[PDB]
Amino acid sequence: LSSIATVSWQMGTEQSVRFNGYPAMELSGSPATGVSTGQAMEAVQKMVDE
Amino acid sequence: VGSALSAQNIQISAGSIGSLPAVRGQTVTATVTAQGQLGTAEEFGNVILR
Image (cartoon, rainbow over all chains, first blue to last red; front, side, top):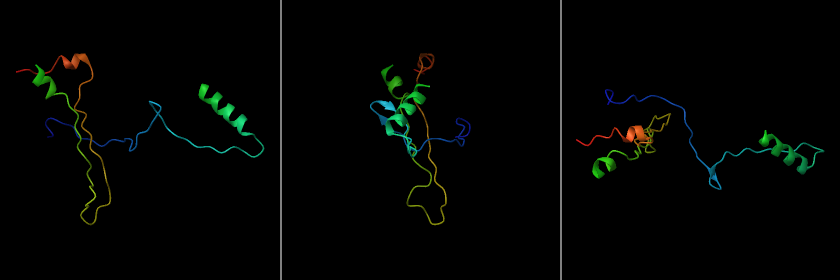
């Protein structure tokens, strides 16, 4: 098998997810004390728009 | 043509290396990947018929 293939070590994902038909990756967060959830959500949306 | 195209473009599922029966003393697990499919036309044009 060495004369036809090149088996080698590699780094790869061990779990795959999809949300509404598109590949998705989930990350969590926690708002700081004194800041409303609406501001946090707007900031996250702006960052995503970045 | 049909047989050559169908017996030469197929996915391979190779499994894992440290399967769970796991003869005593095993300390690591891996995964094996093949990718035996064709994606572009310049390589569909190189299939072997005879």
